[PDB]
Image (cartoon, coloured by chain):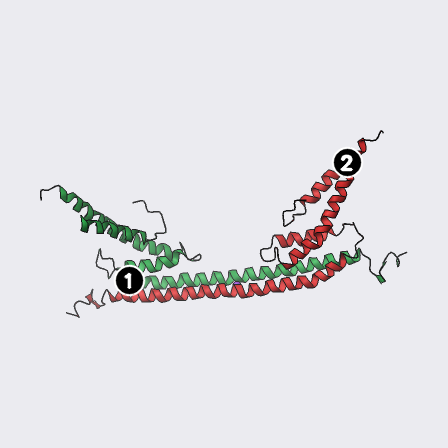
Chain colours: A green, B red
């Protein structure tokens, strides 16, 4: 009868209830455990979205100090390249800020200033190799090495063909 | 003199100070911005490490209810497979808990129970195809489809050859 179709090893436990019950409990453990992962993911995002917004904003307020220091610059003078190096070397290996609003502004603000320096040193090596056309190399090689060393240390974030 | 080697557009700003200053400021913005990323990463970890520990622990306390429901089981009866399906389908697509302590226990607790069912249905199809040896197929095909449907829905986390 019902009581005997229920008795196992001296205890009244329908083995299809001790399973149907274990199921519903597993259902609840899973749901709590997932809800916990959702909470963690969602808080990560909130704090992230806000800290990136904060970073992009404080970089704007800094930009004005940078844009301003790059007009006090005598034209075709490039002791401002260490600034681009420091700033771009941080932003490019930064998941959050790479190609962000400030990064693109730092590229634009320096994109003419970089080409106006390579065109100026490529014209001073081209003239010096063309100096063998009028009648009457060690120092010249250094300027090739200088331009190559410079270009490699630029780690430019685009693909600049020309 | 010093005052004139300083005057630009009516303001006494050494253009190599308005750069050296912009540099040190960029140094500080970068450091704060990175410190902020470090904080976020580190808190993510703390909360993560603790929520995984919490999950693995509450799965232990559940295991005893599961280990217990799998001895109240009449040998070679498999309405306990929907439990493995629910639990394993969650754990396997869960970055944190996959192949964790509980996941491996759920594999072990069901690894004999799965092979003891395929060997039992592979022996009941092999006998029925071997029934064409004594003198004197539609229903038999269903059991192949049943075993294939079962095996695919198992999504076992190892590579079980045999
Ligand atoms: K977090």
User: Which sits in the foreground, B112 or A86?
Assistant: B112
Q: Are marks 1 and 2 in contact (CB under 8 Å)?
A: no
Q: Position of residue A8 (x, y in %)?
A: 84, 59
Q: Name the residue under label 1.
A: A68
Q: Which of marks 1 and 2 is in front?
A: 2
Q: In which quarter of the image is residue A87?
A: bottom left
Q: Which residue is drawn at 25% across and 51% down?
A: A145
Q: Where is residue B21 in the image (x, y as percent from the top left)?
A: 29, 67
Q: Provide the secondary structure element on which disc 2 rests.
A: helix
Q: Residue at x 25, y 67 (%)?
A: B17
User: Which sits in the foreground, A77 or B9?
Assistant: A77
Q: Where is residue B144 in the image (x, y as percent from the top left)?
A: 73, 38
Q: Provide the secondary structure element on which disc 1 rests.
A: helix
Residue extending farthest to the right is: A1
Residue extending farthest to the top is: B135
CA separation in Å, label 1 and label 2: 84 Å
* Chain name for mark 1: A
Q: Where is residue B50 in the image (x, y as percent from the top left)?
A: 58, 65
Question: In the image, is A39 to the left or to the right of A117?
Answer: right
Q: Which mark is residue B140?
A: 2
* Chain name for mark 2: B
């Amino acid at each position: 009868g019902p009581l005997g179709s229920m008795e196992n090893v001296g205890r009244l436990i329908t083995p299809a209830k001790k399973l149907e019950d274990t199921i519903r409990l597993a259902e609840l453990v899973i749901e709590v455990l997932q809800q916990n992962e959702e909470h963690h993911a969602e808080a990560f995002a909130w704090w992230s979205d806000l800290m990136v917004e904060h970073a992009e904003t404080f970089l704007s307020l800094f930009a004005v100090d940078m844009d301003a220091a790059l007009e006090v610059q005598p034209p075709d003078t490039w002791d401002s390249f260490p600034l681009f190096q420091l700033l771009n070397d941080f932003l490019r290996t930064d998941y959050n800020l790479c190609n962000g609003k400030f990064h693109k502004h730092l590229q634009d603000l320096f994109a003419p200033l970089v080409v106006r320096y390579v065109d100026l040193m490529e014209s001073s090596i081209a003239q010096s190799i063309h100096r063998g056309f009028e009648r009457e190399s060690e120092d010249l090689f250094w300027k090739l090495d200088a331009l190559q060393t410079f270009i490699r240390d630029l780690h430019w974030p685009e693909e600049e063909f020309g």
